[PDB]
Structure formats: C-alpha cells, structure tokens
Length: 354
Ligand SMILES: [Mn+2]
Image 1 (cartoon, protein in one colour):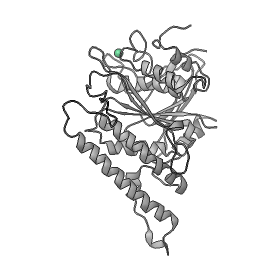
Image 2 (cartoon, rainbow, N blue to C red):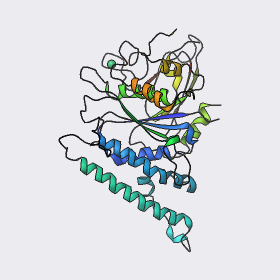
Image 3 (cartoon, rainbow, N blue to C red):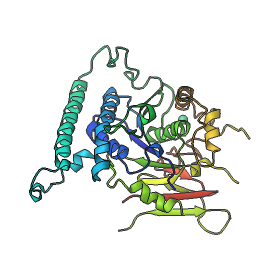
Image 4 (cartoon, rainbow, N blue to C red):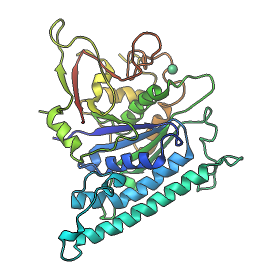
C-alpha cells in the first residue's frame, strides 16, 4: 500500500537560487507517479521574496498543463528544462503522431512559461520604494525581510482547480515563517523544523522527503520504489525496529537530503500533555496518530490558523525543537545542523534516491 509523503523544499534567495530551477524541481514533484492525494509539496521561502511567491503561483498554473501531459505519455525526466534537452528522433515517424503535436504544443507553452518567469526576475531586479504590491492591490507582507508575519498559501490540491484533463493535482504549499528582530531563525534548520510542524498540521504524512531546490526527481516512480522498501552503484537504505539495549543500532541516526524517512522517528516516544513540542494542541495530536493524517472534522481554515501559529517566531522557545527534536541547531558540539534526528527508541526507515 502507498503511504502519504510530505516533500520539503527550502529556498532563501531568488538571486542565487534561480526561480526557474526551483520551478523545475517543483514540477518534477507535482508530476510524480503516485496517488495525487498522498503526495504534498511544501516550499519554505526563508527570503519571503515576492519573486519566489509569484514564480510558485506561475509554476502551479503551468503544472496544470504539464502534469497530465507527463502522466499520459510516460515522460521522463518530469522536469521540463531537462526533458526538452533530450534530443528526439523525429525521423522515425512517417507522419506527425498525436504525441508529437501534443509535445510541440507543450514545449511552446513551456517556452512561454520561461518568458514570464524571466519577466518576474527582471521586474524584481530593481526594488520599488514603497515596497512590492500584490497583483491584488494589497501590500506584500514579505517586504521587510527580517520583520514580517507568518505566511502560508496553498495552491492546487483539492480546491485549486483541475489539470487539463479535469483531474486534481497535489497540494503545493508556500510557507514563509515569521521573522522578528530579537529571535533567531537558525537558517535552513529552523526552516526544516517549521516545515515539519506545518506539514503535520495540514497533511501529516507518515513519510518525509527533503529535496534541495535544484534536485529534480529523475524518475517519476521514485516514491513507489521507495515504498517497495519502506513497507514490506546501489542506493542508501536503512530499517530498524529498536526494542532493546545493547543489540543492533545504538543511538540516533541523522538523515539529510534526498531521503524518504518515517515521520514518527523525529518525535521521541517510548512504547502526558507536556509541551516539549511547544504549545499547539493540534500538533501534538498529530504526533499521536497511527498512520498520519488529519481529523477530517477540521475545516481548511482554522487549521490554516494553527499552521500559522506553529511558524510563529517564538514557537520553539522552551521546547526541545533544535535541541533534541527535528533538525538540530549547531555550533556547540553536535556536528549537525546537517540532518533530521531519528531517535533509536522506535521504528525507523530510510530510502535514499541515487
Ligand atoms: Mn530558537
């Protein structure tokens, strides 16, 4: 069977992380050969850059065309830039097939997509003074980069409008955690932790996968192959049920990038209310769930509220986050801010892609 997966991408600066490359990674994620309902893509933008937000909006709109195309004709890789670079043998066909016209159409619409991304970049290339204004008319909450409220925006998924074939697409969530003067944010680490919490509130998939913003998925089946190991040259795998003391794997394991791993390993918990996890009833509830998921009773809105709450600024204060929970904040000794901490304690599984 196929378990839900939450996929994290972290970006920080559109000027060293070109929006188009991020777009291609995201498009490779949204087109993944896996049940649409059970794959979700969270994109932390630590820079709160409207260029990124809009590029992401654009990306989702293009995904509406690109994803059904890929699934219909079994395309790989499912990141457009690298797909259209693979040379094709047109000579082998006597006449234009339906595939190649679908595809010439598609490439054209992708080149148009690129053009509007370039437009966004260039438009951004010199600061307006009164700050950026949304296509709405309301001011952009991210303009003050070290001083701005939490932002979450969900694209696609169940109420983000179908693809070109009337089918739904995976959730695509924009997240920019609160930044305030006087609070540390611990960089990518504090970002991964906040994404753990947000994803827990919105979807709560039993597995997590963290990809760099330039790591596009090579093979649309990557998640299925991973599940072929996670539930009963070569790549990195790890499985452990650790009862026990002295036998087997001792202590924590640290997982970085490109690896599907089980969520609950993050959480401590030997087989109490205690806010070790910070104060959010919804979140700890989520940590106490068998096979992940949210209570369907909750409505998209008020859980959007608690999702904004778990990325507030000082949520982690007086909590184990960054200390013994999640991605671990460094410069003391641990030699981390390099991975998610998987506690020995209980069930642990990792499948990494090549
Ligand atoms: Mn802190």
